[PDB]
Amino acid sequence: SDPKLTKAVDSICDQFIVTKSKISQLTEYFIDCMEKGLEPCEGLPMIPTFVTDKPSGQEHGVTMLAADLGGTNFRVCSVELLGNHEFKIEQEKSKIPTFFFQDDHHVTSKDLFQHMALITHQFLTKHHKDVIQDYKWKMGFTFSYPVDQTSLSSGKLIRWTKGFKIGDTVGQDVVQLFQQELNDIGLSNVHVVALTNDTTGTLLARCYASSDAARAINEPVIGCIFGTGTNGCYMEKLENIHKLDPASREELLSQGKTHMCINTEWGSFDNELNHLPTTSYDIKIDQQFSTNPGFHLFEKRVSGLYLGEILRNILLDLEKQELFDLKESVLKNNPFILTTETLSHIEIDTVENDLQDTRDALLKAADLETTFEERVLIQKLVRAISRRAAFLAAVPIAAILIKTNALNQSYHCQVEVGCDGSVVEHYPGFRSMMRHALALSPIGPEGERDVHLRISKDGSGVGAALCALHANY
Amino acid sequence: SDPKLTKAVDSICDQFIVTKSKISQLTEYFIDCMEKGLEPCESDISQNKGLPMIPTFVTDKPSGQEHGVTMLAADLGGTNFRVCSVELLGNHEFKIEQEKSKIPTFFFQDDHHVTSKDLFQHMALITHQFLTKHHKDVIQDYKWKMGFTFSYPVDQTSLSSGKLIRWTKGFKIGDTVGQDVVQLFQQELNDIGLSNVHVVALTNDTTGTLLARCYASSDAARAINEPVIGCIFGTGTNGCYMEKLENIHKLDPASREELLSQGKTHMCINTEWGSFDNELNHLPTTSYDIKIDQQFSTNPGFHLFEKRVSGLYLGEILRNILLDLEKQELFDLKESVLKNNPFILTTETLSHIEIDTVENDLQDTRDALLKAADLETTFEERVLIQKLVRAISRRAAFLAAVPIAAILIKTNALNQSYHCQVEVGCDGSVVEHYPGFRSMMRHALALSPIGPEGERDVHLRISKDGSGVGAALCALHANY
């Protein structure tokens, strides 16, 4: 209907295409960054988590509690391990005040961890009134942030993310700080025994929830997240974790341990952009509309937070060319007004319904009245953004499986990949497009059929509880 | 160690291979038998060369968001009677209470003058006893909708009307033959004061496997991930799917039009694919499949496809191969007890061999054969026995995939949306528990006409208890 605008959209969509050649390149380059990352500091982060055992699913008769500090909520839960892949969970939820995300000179780290301590006291008083001060509680702490973890219960914050501005916390042991405030309110009997990442929890949770005899050939190997951010972990041979001091590496091998879970934090993959597909829109977003410019570049191309923003910048560039009319819309100066959920309604909308689900999504999101011919092109852009995100999201998984020869161990060898996150859970077709990229990746179609992307929820709870199980009070 | 025996086994293993060329042939021939089976009776063949293709009269699928309601189900097997209550909690979750009971021996006696009334009166009392136990307070107020699972040959004329054809599994009640079992069961439910319990549905256990997965399909949104097939792969096999009302030409036009007038568009078809290609025009066949179908079978000449996929016969096939290898002085059975003990080799025995590794001298296989038939073996023998087991199981999984691929192709299930995906509800000792069976099925699906891109959009998820929860869910969308 409008050949001028149409040709413009066709050109932009082609910039988001990820060819089989590129998947091979990025998969090979990812393994290179993996090995470089396993060396002493001077590649990927590659952070040892010090988790060496996998839950069997038969741990029972014990009750653990765990604390999870997300980006917008604080969470306290109690996980009763009942064995047979079943568990009871009770919890109390608390919001994080908004003044912690601004750089108020009056807000400090202590005020944050004191907030966490009081909620613990309020939660324990709610469900376990009789054992609040006597029980020898073992607590698992899920701190889904960049951390330089030196042991299972010691980790200093490296840098805040997800909109946080508290400088006094950086470079300080977050577990000890949290423990300092738990003693002050009279809960000295609560010992923070484990410091885990949310990916480490996603994996252990699926190990406990997996099947007894199916796991003889179907072993969970990766725990990853695809939501506001992205990150993944896997088990690595102790011999390859050169960051680990040899004494501790030797001590674990002599104890029957063979692997240790590595928190790759692959969101920081190829921060130099030697190979990641990049467009003027990814650059304009990385420098201006980013909270930590220059960091987590791979995450910004796959995170559900930035997917909506990418579309917005495309439309603004199209208005600059007098091709698209925003009229009374409110996109001109409203970053992140386009959300991952908004695009979801566009992904699966049908042209048989004049793309009605998309018109309403745009009106509700930015009062942007549209025509049928416009939504058809907007749909093409959304489907191209999601497809690149799903294709890139497959590279880390394929690289990890290749580097560990997980797919060729037995006659009927299969592997599971635990996933959690608004994108992979609910964004329509995301997993479907991931499986497609896995088929185009070096593992091949025969490799994908032996890979199962099963979703495992509540990693920050059961997973953190299991880490405290094998820890000493 | 023995090149003669090795070469013999490699030749036998090659007889069980199913090539991509064959998968296309069988998938295409299956759809032909599907269409022939849907035509009016008495055409070329007495009832068409095609499959049975039996309408179940189930037209609605649970959405998974139904809540606040409790449904009942009754299941009459060969040796037990079962009554359960399924409370739907929405969000793909549900509560289930049940009581299972043995069938009194008085029904198996001779000369006692047993009649249908005596049987359904017992079922009514058991139902009343169950409702008094778990739903004491609402037994007489609730408008209970019950689904009836009657595991016997039935001529189903509607969703709630079906006449018994013949007793099986050791039953002798003449009053039942040719009578609506739903009406009989309903007659006695009214007498004991449960007139408010309406048997609204008479269901098959395969149809329930599908409906059960419809409610439990929580992973994907149904806008693009719709369950389409419910099948069974255990001792027997069978599957079902939704067919357009217009293609069920055997269906009476009067009943067909009335359903169209209610907004219904599809009806679940009980294919009974176990009887697929009983003429063996194309089904892979070996001397072992023939000797087992005629001698060690209970119904020779019938259910040929079922005997190629049933977990019961997989172990037997191995036995006949080893006996044939001993008859040729190639394999030494020694003190084994295979000579006259059919089915002594079970699917469970083969399971330990399927995934056993040669890195451990195949010890799980050495032990499995000793416990099963006191057959002492050598390492070189177990290597070949494993090759035979893995070849037999692979043929069964490849053949089990043909019907699924055939149904998906005939219904364009994979080409409905941009991100269209489908689920297949499965139950059965073989598909559920035989190691790798599901994995080899997906491989055959990739080699089938749907292609590898089609397999990635097919999900073989397991849905248990079709004759209980499934029968209850069928009654959900049925009218009181």
Image (cartoon, coloured by chain):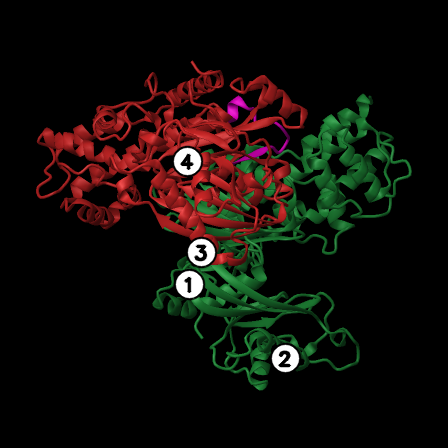
Chain colours: A red, B green
The reply to whether the magenta stretch includes residue A411 is yes
What span is in magenta?
A: A401-417
For mark 2, name the chain: B
The percent position of residue B28, horizontal first and vertical second, equals 51, 42
The quarter holding residue A184 reads: top left
Q: What is the secondary structure assignment of the residue under circle 1?
A: loop
Amino acid type at mark 1: Glu
| Closer-to-camera residue (B95/B216) | B95
Relative side of B277 to A401, left or right? right
Q: Label 1 belongs to which residue?
A: B66
Q: Label 3 belongs to which residue?
A: B243
The reply to whether the magenta stretch includes residue A270 is no
Residue B313 seen from this side: yes
Question: Which tag, 3 or 2, sits closer to the chain's start?
Answer: 2
Relative side of B184 to B371, left or right? left
Q: Label 4 belongs to which residue?
A: A144
Q: Do labels 2 and 1 share a chain?
A: yes
Residue B413 seen from this side: no
Seen at 41% across and 35% down, the residue is: A144
Relative side of A215 to B55, left or right? right
Q: What is the secondary structure assignment of the residue under circle 3?
A: strand
Q: Nearer the viewer, mark 1 or mark 4?
A: 4
Q: How far apart are marks 1 and 4 (CA)?
A: 37 Å
Q: Quadrant of the C terminus of chain A?
A: top right
Q: Which of marks 4 and 3 is in front?
A: 4
| Closer-to-camera residue (A55/B55) | A55
Q: How far apart are marks 1 and 3 (CA)?
A: 24 Å
Amino acid type at mark 3: Glu
The percent position of residue B472, horizontal first and vertical second, equals 52, 66
